Length: 17
Image 1: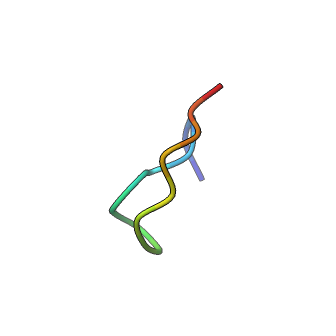
Image 2: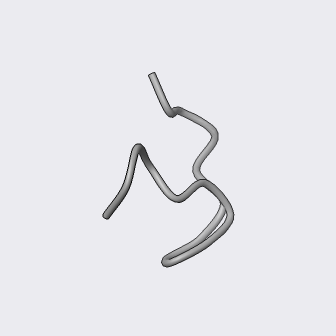
Image 3: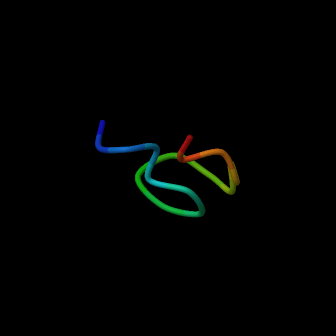
């Protein structure tokens, strides 16, 4: 549940904003 854990702790979600 960090900045967006893009490609981690969930999945690939390029969008840290």
